[PDB]
Image 1 (cartoon, rainbow, N blue to C red):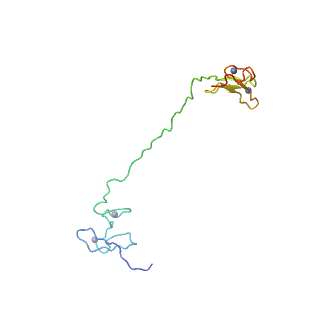
Image 2 (cartoon, rainbow, N blue to C red):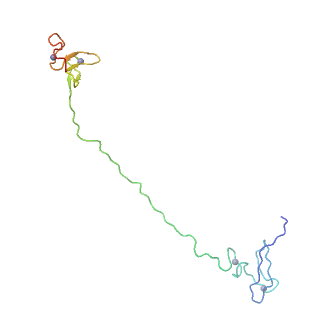
Length: 141
Ligand SMILES: [Zn+2]
Ligand SMILES: [Zn+2]
Ligand SMILES: [Zn+2]
Ligand SMILES: [Zn+2]
């Protein structure tokens, strides 16, 4: 560090002085050692102090001051009802062979048992086995 510079100076605040005070950047002690020697501040006439200071007022009336915390809820309820009343009907008649529920086909008066292990045809109007008696006399809708 070898650079010649200068910092902000000040003057003796005495009405009978004003000779001039030279304040070095690394100097923290202002005193009229050349005249009416008394210690004061470089920014104010507080008689020297440590900290901040600004001439003609700092311009600080307020800043920040607020402390308050709130609690949440996170509490709720949940419900649901599935259903009520179940009416079941029967549209099927038991097969004469496998006894499986055979349903009718609207539009035709013939119904055959379509079952994996059956395949038994019978008359809808008069339920009987497919024979010569009712070979389909009225097998037409
Ligand atoms: Zn002085
Ligand atoms: Zn000061
Ligand atoms: Zn059957
Ligand atoms: Zn018949």
